Structures are given as structure tokens and as C-alpha cells.
Amino acid sequence: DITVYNGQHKEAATAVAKAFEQETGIKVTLNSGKSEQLAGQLKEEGDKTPADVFYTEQTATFADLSEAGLLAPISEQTIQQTAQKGVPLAPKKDWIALSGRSRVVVYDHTKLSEKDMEKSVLDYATPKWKGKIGYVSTSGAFLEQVVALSKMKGDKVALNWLKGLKENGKLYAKNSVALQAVENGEVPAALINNYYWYNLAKEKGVENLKSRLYFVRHQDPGALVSYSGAAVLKASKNQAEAQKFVDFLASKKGQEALVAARAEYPLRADVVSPFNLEPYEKLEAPVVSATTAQDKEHAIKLIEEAGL
Ligand SMILES: [Fe+3]
Ligand SMILES: [Fe+3]
Ligand SMILES: [Fe+3]
């Protein structure tokens, strides 16, 4: 039996653990919390940690644990199961990316079509979109989008986009609220993440929704994907079962369990999502370094400077 420190949505972690317990008869205990807190906890606990595996919604969390000497190596055959082009790889082969969440533009297809969409996420912050684009500045993925713009295009561009959103956009408290505002006609488009929309479609039926998604693709900064993953702790004295679990998460079965539970993109090429997601490779995500705590502080500074 193993202990998994879990920064992922509880429904995802519960599903894969259950599927694993059913496939192997090995029991999984979840300890759930915020990935950054769990990573600090793993650092402080050190050799004495009870965690066998760290399962996170954000692979960026692994860099600091790897450099601290806290992660075990995983099988290269396992790493290769999800190593599609563009998927982040651990240089020390001591964690693996398993699934992804995408930035997207949601639009009311009763008012707009693809003719009205933009080639670049930058172009939504422009006067064409005054009072017509919703955004969620408090959102973690909004903050990852800002980090990506800084990285890909520089701070001037990033700041200018934020000022453009201040001037032209409608601020919503959360992604679900933005999505509802588009469905309800308050605003004709909004910047959100994919799974909100696919959750609502699965639940209500797409034919009954007024909104649709637009993917910018071509490695635009607005095609940003955030990656979930897993690592074995070097401190574990149950390496065999920890390793068996991380192998399971990369298996067809483990990926199928995840995608049934949550509308994340599987990183195995032979798994479909019942949420009707496109294949990961079609997203054309840009390649962006992992977010650091310094990157996040910097992005928060730009958001403040833009009056947001
Ligand atoms: Fe959430
Ligand atoms: Fe949310
Ligand atoms: Fe969210």
C-alpha cells in the first residue's frame, strides 16, 4: 500500500487511485493539498517523509524537488509512454508529465463565428474587443498566461496586453462565472481554460449550449498548456509499489481512468477522452519553461502595474 501527496483535483486522484487499487489490489492513501504547500512539506520532511508518490496538477513543482535531490528515477520506458512532441521531459528522468489543461477562448456562436476570432491571444486586448472580452485576473492559469507572454514576447508586450485587458475587457471573479456570462449573453467571448467548457457540455449537451471553443494553435502564447504529472520520492522505502503506481498512471488503463474523471488531455496517443477533447498534438502548444516562484512574483508585479 502507498501514500500519495496529491495536488491534483480530488476527483482525478480518487479515480486513478481507485482504478489502481482495482487493477493491482494495492491500496492508495491520498494526502491532498495545494501543490506548493505539499512540495514544501516534502522538502521539510526529507528522509522521513511518508509520501511514496507526489501527484501534481503542475509539473513546474518538480524542478525544485529534483534539484534538492528528493526524487527517484523512473523507467525510461515509462517516460516514453507520454513523450509526445512538446511534452516537458525531466532532464534527470525523475518525474513524468501525464496530462494537460489548455487556455482557450470561449465564444457565443449565436453572435460570433471564427471570422471574428484572432490569430493571437494578444489581439483580444484591443479596442475591437471593448466591453466584449471576459477575463479572470485572479485565476492561476491567467497568471501562467502572463508568465508565458513575458517569456515568449517580453515584458513590454505582456504589460501592454494587461493594460489592454484593463481598458477593453470585462473582469469576472472565476472561470465558471466568465463561461456563464458568455452563455447568458453578457459578453460574447472570454479567456478561460478548456475543461470548464467541456464539463458544461458533457453535463448539458453541446446542442443545448450557446458557447463554443476557439483554439488559437500554431504555438501562439494563447495555446499554452499546463501539465499535470507524477514523481516517486527518493525517501520512499516502497520503491517497487511507488514505481508500479507511476507506471500505471502512464499506462493505457491509467490514462483512461484519468480522462473519464476530468477533462484533461491525455498524453498517451492511443487514449480518447469521453469529454470529446481534440488530440493533444493538434493543440500546437508553445514550448515554455516551467513556472518558478520568481516568475510568479514577477507576473503578479505586472498585473499590479497594469492597474489590475
Ligand atoms: Fe479547479
Ligand atoms: Fe476553477
Ligand atoms: Fe481551474
Image (cartoon, rainbow, N blue to C red):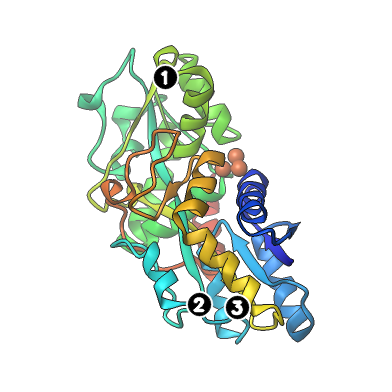
> For the N terminus, which image quadrant?
bottom right
Left or right, 235 with reference to 162: right
Please indicate, yes or no, whether residue 159 appears anywhere in the rendered image.
Answer: yes
Work out whether mark 1 precedes mark 2 in sequence or the reverse, and give the earlier one.
Answer: 2
Work out whether mark 3 precedes mark 1 in sequence or the reverse, and give the earlier one.
Answer: 3
Q: Is residue 291 above or below residue 213?
A: below
Cβ of mark 2 under 8 A from ligand 1:
no
The residue under label 2 is which amino acid type? Answer: Ile
- The one nearer the camera, 160 or 12, is 12
At 39% across and 33% down in the image, what residue appears? 276
Q: Position of residue 12 (x, y in %)?
A: 60, 47
Please indicate, yes or no, whether residue 293 appears anywhere in the rendered image.
Answer: no
At 39% across and 14% down in the image, what residue appears? 207
Label 3 crowd (10 A; few <14 / some 14-19 / many >=20): some
Question: Which callout, 1 or 2, points to the residue nearer the camera?
Answer: 2
Which mark, by number, is residue 134? none
Residue that mark 3 sits on:
65
Question: Which callout, 2 or 3, points to the residue nearer the camera?
Answer: 2
Residue that mark 1 sits on:
206
Residue that mark 2 sits on:
74
Q: Report the label total.
A: 3
The residue under label 3 is which amino acid type? Answer: Leu
> For the C terminus, which image quadrant?
top right
Per the image, label 1 sits on a secondary structure element best described as helix
Q: Position of residue 60 (x, y in %)?
A: 51, 67
Work out whether mark 2 precedes mark 3 in sequence or the reverse, and give the earlier one.
Answer: 3
* Alpha carbon distance from label 1 to label 2: 40 Å
Cβ of mark 1 under 8 A from ligand 3:
no
At 49% across and 56% down in the image, what residue appears? 302
Cβ of mark 3 under 8 A from ligand 1:
no
* Alpha carbon distance from label 3 to label 1: 41 Å
